[PDB]
Amino acid sequence: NTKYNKEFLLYLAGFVDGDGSIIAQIKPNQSYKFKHQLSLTFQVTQKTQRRWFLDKLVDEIGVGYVRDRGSVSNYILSEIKPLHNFLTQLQPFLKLKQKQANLVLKIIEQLPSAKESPDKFLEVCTWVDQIAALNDSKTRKTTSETVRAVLD
Amino acid sequence: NTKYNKEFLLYLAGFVDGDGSIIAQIKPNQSYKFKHQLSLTFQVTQKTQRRWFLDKLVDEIGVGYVRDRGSVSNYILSEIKPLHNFLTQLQPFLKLKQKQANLVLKIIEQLPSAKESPDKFLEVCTWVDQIAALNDSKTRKTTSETVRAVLD
DNA sequence: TCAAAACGTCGTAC
DNA sequence: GACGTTTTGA
DNA sequence: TCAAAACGTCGTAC
DNA sequence: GACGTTTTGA
Ligand SMILES: [Mg+2]
Ligand SMILES: [Mg+2]
Ligand SMILES: [Mg+2]
Ligand code: NA
């Protein structure tokens, strides 16, 4: 796992606290044992005319990709291992999004265990609730309650 | 002149590039010799529920203030001397807003001479045009062209 | 006559 | 910014 | 059954 | 985020 430079992390942390997102999702999906996917995403959003900025992020992070949705574009990192490595290093410098970052870390490390028991899986969905609670969440639909209602 | 930590400036630069604004305005105002005020503003916006972040900033920058504006709040720095001192030190770390930062500095250093001649005043106004051209400017009204007419 | 503050509005870029 | 639904390709 | 990508919309918080 | 109009107080 690559070691990121501190100056880079410091600036990136600031910019993430401003225009980034640390996202956790429970995605209803019939092909999973517990009928839901656990989905983590690190994202940085910027007007497409400045997507060169996001393209640099890819070079500097060395992983992830940029997707253009129209007037706006996103840097995206969803790969679990690279995500853990990156957040572990960024986390210390976050001020607005530190708890979310850490909750993500906690979730990733427990995934293996969440696969085993419906209970441990339900607990983990709770951590996702905390992430969403900390964020400026407005259009969320699938929660730990949703999972509890399905595991029956 | 108060001298800021690099760790501080690096994180703040990222956050500014994200959620900050470097604003230059020509404010129509009859009480001025050229019938407009030159206004410089450094601004950071954030949901009012995260005020404390902005309030911390005031302590850390040691100058400026926070204004709650309903559901959103703002850190503001308008005083010219601290603004020059702060921007001079922040500028090396901005990626998105570095050019307007340098333009603000130039304007500040020229203000005195700009008050002497309408021609120099006009030129300075063209630099504020440049700052607005760099920003995601959408509702601008007063430009150097409008100053130009008035001085006629 | 000026620097600075007070207060308000708009259209996205998050 | 922070979600959503559905598809891919193991 | 899964990790990850593809693709889309909502409601502000810039 | 990035403007706008109007007021304060030396
Ligand atoms: Mg923000
Ligand atoms: Mg931004
Ligand atoms: Mg923003
Ligand atoms: Na904006």
Image (cartoon, coloured by chain):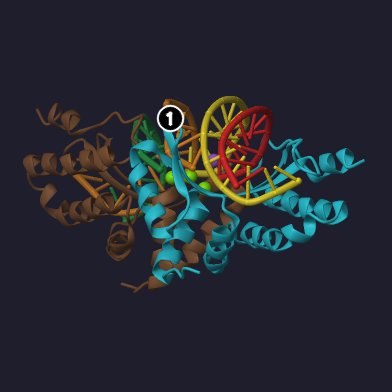
Chain colours: A brown, B cyan, C yellow, D green, E orange, F red
Q: Mark 1 lies on which chain?
A: B
Give the image quarter of residue A7.
Answer: bottom left
**What residue is shown with label 1?**
B70
Residue beneath the point at 92% across and 40% down:
B152
Q: Is residue E10 placed above or below B30 in the rendered structure?
A: above
Q: Is residue B145 left or right of residue A100?
A: right
Question: Where in the figure is residue B27, as x and y percent of width and height?
Answer: 71, 40
Relative to B67, F9 lies left or right: right
Above or below, comparing residue A148 to residue B26 in the picture: above
Determine if residue B115 is in view.
yes
Using the image as rendered, state which of residue A92 and residue A81 is in the foreground.
Answer: A92
Pick the residue in front: B55 or A82.
B55
Going 57% across and 50% down the picture, which residue do you hit?
B78
* In this picture, residue A135 sits left or right of residue B122: left
Residue type beneath disc 1: Gly
Q: Is residue A43 something one can see in this rendering?
A: no
Q: Is B96 or B144 nearer to us in this picture?
A: B144
